[PDB]
Image 1: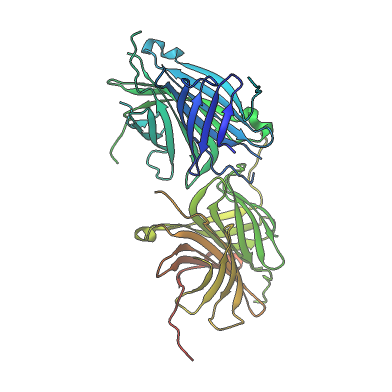
Image 2 (image 1 turned 135 degrees about the horizontal axis):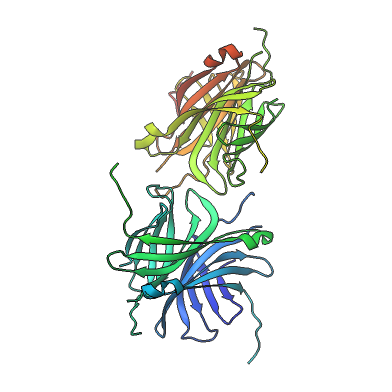
Length: 125
Length: 125
Length: 125
Length: 125
């Protein structure tokens, strides 16, 4: 369900493998189609989401925004849940912290949200 | 600097290895001294934090709260920065998402903060 | 008499059906009001407690502390008797065994007691 | 491992099925070879005994001492752990409660121990 490719509503993508141990491993591409905008992703998910009391599957992952083309001196974490079915989604909140000086630490962290889907509008060239 | 053991101010610990590739890998122990409260951690950090414009080192990690003794059907992500020196710290914000039904998704995510230090008050038995 | 809900003096509850065959079947909730603290219960009772020589009704049950949220790798058994009337009670002794290594088997089993009643102090929110 | 027949060191036997859900279901024969000494058993076991911190498998069961030939107005619970291998064993503590009058409740419960093995000395007739 989680393994595969996901698209947010703003032009980013990621590919992830959800391993049997609870691992998430993949790559995050901040600009669809841009080969230079790819960063390592790692995280964790609930590998036994069933309960006796249709709940989503909790997960989280991190991207540090450093690759061979960019270093934004920052990292984002996404916390959310996977929901399967016909309109499968990963609903997330995220936090983006930048390294700062001490005087600027108060303003080191942005918050937002991303909704990831398995499909996005697409069209021929 | 980041590799080693960290303590929050509430009785949790984690041990982490910061690899040369930007990887963070370790274990998180939600109750100090409790062998049953240990969970896998994985994340990422800025492996080249220097800039030309003393900033902290951005990082993030995830713990899914599933191990052989517990499954809280939830995961926390911590986003923050490492600050070295004499009172080295990892200052973080965190998000804790639980799997929920759709009707309860609005209340799936808690937010907080943790400050991690390399030492905590300690005392002989 | 036995069928119904019972409260110990420490915040736990259980619900049980005493079947005509001597079966006890229900659920044990280790923390009142906590939907994640519910475990299967099974046991047996004396389905013909009358004698010619007002005695209680002998019973026993087991809870293994494994559900979809926890696995304490342990099980409790309660052995006791039901006493009816105006202050009906189930007076029990219990044994809690944890799986251990062989070197630790000597310390695998705790003993205690629980008194269950049909009512507990209660109050509006 | 647990499913099958077990012998204590005093002439009793039981047969049990350990179900995939954590159930134990079987019969307890208090006198080997005596068809009139058979009673229903029910209990629970840890159906995922693995930990990351060779431990035994916790379990417990109850026998009410009522069948079509006897009613001792009492029930035994056994609490213990299964240990596999070449000399597989179930090491237990037990509690035997009898229904009593209120004045006699103090003396309602016996305690002991039983070690169950998969084999016992045996011999041709």
